[PDB]
Length: 227
Ligand SMILES: [Ca+2]
Ligand SMILES: [Ca+2]
Ligand SMILES: [Ca+2]
Ligand SMILES: [Zn+2]
Ligand SMILES: [Zn+2]
Image (cartoon, rainbow, N blue to C red; front, top):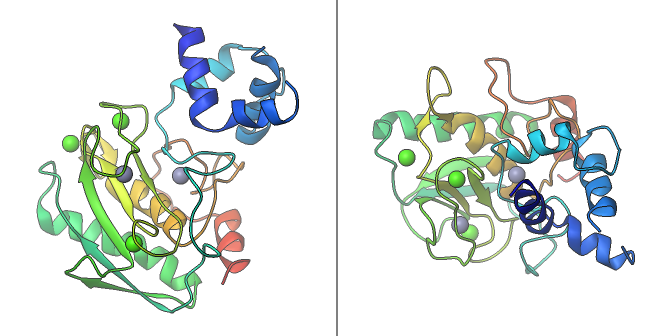
């Protein structure tokens, strides 16, 4: 099943598709993954690569996209609105509200965007907690594995951010995953950022708890090179 995990991972995150497009066994796809995740480029299902595959992470693909999306995948207005459609029961509602507010506050300081909480589906960014299949055909996977996902700027589902409520949500101390950190990362996608290959960057796909400021140069330059 180590081969099972590797196959599913390489497929889910887009490595197998790219390997096919290059006329190429797991080796070539592992190599692409190793390059993408900044692991040693051995092309082998080795210990570092298996460990990486076992690490909880964002459900957004690394190469390619969930699907074909509408538009150019950046916002064309400045006041982005968001709606917290539902709540996890893991944290008080006020703490969840504030986690999301603080996550947006990270991006607002480094972009010409502002973020405004609203209370309707008309919001640019709809935020949902869900489990397994939760209405968008990209089902969550139960405890651990993928923690959340989001969709690039645009109409409808685009711009939305979903969190897997089969995870224990906390602020990352003690037990559970930091909703603040995961939200900060997902909002990045919701603004049009892709994954970073820099392991310390906020937009690196793997979950990494830290008490330090979440943004790194790579995240700031990424958003600068967009807006
Ligand atoms: Ca999960
Ligand atoms: Ca939306
Ligand atoms: Ca939960
Ligand atoms: Zn992501
Ligand atoms: Zn979803």
